[PDB]
Amino acid sequence: MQIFVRTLTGRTITLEVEPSDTIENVRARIQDREGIPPDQQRLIFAGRQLEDGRTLSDYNIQRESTLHLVLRLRGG
Image 1 (cartoon, rainbow, N blue to C red):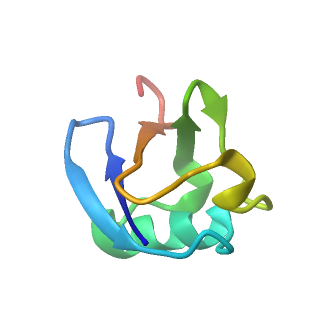
Image 2: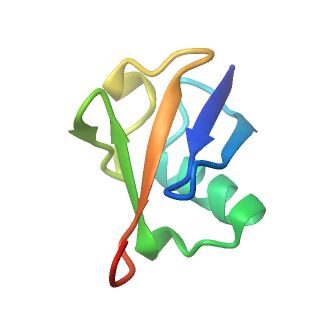
């Protein structure tokens, strides 16, 4: 299952994940690409905050789903 992540800067990346994978894992996969610490990531899907401890399936996130990433940095 491939998903999309859009950074605060409007940069879209593609991650290979599974429904049973945690959002924590997704955050790590994002950091692997952008270099953004998971702790500085705010992930939102359908207006809902994506808790790292919960899974993609928990939020009904499927293939070709767009997760929105906001920076927790000052001014982000």
